[PDB]
Image (cartoon, coloured by chain):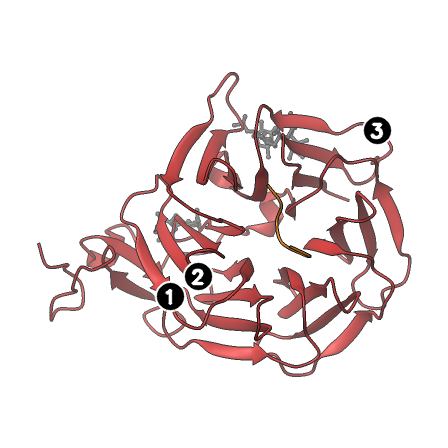
Chain colours: A orange, B red
Amino acid sequence: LPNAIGR
Amino acid sequence: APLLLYANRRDLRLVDATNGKENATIVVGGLEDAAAVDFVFSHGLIYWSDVSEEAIKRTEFNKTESVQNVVVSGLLSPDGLACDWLGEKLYWTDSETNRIEVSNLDGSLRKVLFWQELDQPRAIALDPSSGFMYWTDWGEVPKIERAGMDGSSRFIIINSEIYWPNGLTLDYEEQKLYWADAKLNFIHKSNLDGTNRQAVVKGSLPHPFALTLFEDILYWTDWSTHSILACNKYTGEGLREIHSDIFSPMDIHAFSQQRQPNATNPCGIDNGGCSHLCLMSPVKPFYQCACPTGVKLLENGKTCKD
């Protein structure tokens, strides 16, 4: 999840 | 100093970079998770991705009360998109299906260009009058690649000192590539083939996400500072926050015709004689006919099998 585009 | 167009999850905004203290204007509101953004200035179009609606949409920015219109659907994670304002095409990355795909501006004639050796593709930038496309991948093998805009001649151009390459843009006047790395906290530049790499902003950027350029100034969004920053594109000096308190800044462009300057479309007036897609190409005659996914191009190099 770090750096992932959230929601 | 130009207007800057940025995605902001719930909306797309424009802010004047000479006056980012003022509140941005909302170009399109009521969005769920707008992430990528780009435009075709001459056509009066703005495009964006929505990673919750799993779609690319567009709006007509010179019309009053023009709707949002879905042009591509079923995109699991459309983390990056770029508009080819010359060949009139729409390119995007998908970090869940691990693909780079193109279509016409209306979403028709979809063609997967790359589907191997992608892990976390993200930014994508085009040089239509040279027939090249550039993208980043922040996955297990972090890299910047370029290829023909027709899917030809794919090459890794940066694969060292790289970890979260999020932002990517071109300087069309100087023929330089610029990128921002959110793990290494910097902005670098290189020639278009990756050679002659140089640091611009050497460090101390918390979490840059997207990068654009206008005249002598770089502009980027930062996920940790919730702002747009700027600095000189040669020296990295003059680093200033120009617009802050942004809900969730995402992709960004300098919103100007001069960032999409006029050139001859090598497809001419008859779509290159191509039956389906006429894509920009880095080699003469500087277009290449192409067909939707799964469809074969006949021996003439122009007509897709009907």
Question: Callout 3, which amino acid?
Answer: Glu
User: How far apart are the two marked residues, 1 and 2, measured between alpha carbons?
Assistant: 6 Å
User: How far apart are the two marked residues, 2 and 3, measured between alpha carbons?
Assistant: 39 Å
The N terminus of chain B lies in which quarter of the figure? top right
User: How far apart are the two marked residues, 1 and 3, measured between alpha carbons?
Assistant: 43 Å
Q: Earlier in the sequence, mark 2 or mark 3?
A: 3
Question: Callout 2, which amino acid?
Answer: Asn
Q: State which chain disc 1 sits on.
A: B
Q: Is B48 situated left or right of B180 in this image?
A: left
- Which quadrant of the view contains residue B205? bottom right
Q: State which chain disc 3 sits on.
A: B
Q: Residue at x 66, y 45 (%)?
A: B250
Q: Residue furthest left?
A: B306
Q: Residues within 10 Å of mark 2 (few under 14, many from 20)?
A: many
Q: Which residue is mark 2?
A: B98
Q: Earlier in the sequence, mark 1 or mark 2?
A: 2
Q: Residue at x 61, y 49 (%)?
A: A5
Labels 2, 3: front one:
2
Is circle 1 on the same chain as circle 2? yes
Q: Is B232 situated left or right of B220 in this image?
A: right
The C terminus of chain B lies in which quarter of the figure? bottom left
| Secondary structure category for the residue under label 2 | loop
Residue B193 visible to the viewer: no
| Secondary structure category for the residue under label 3 | loop
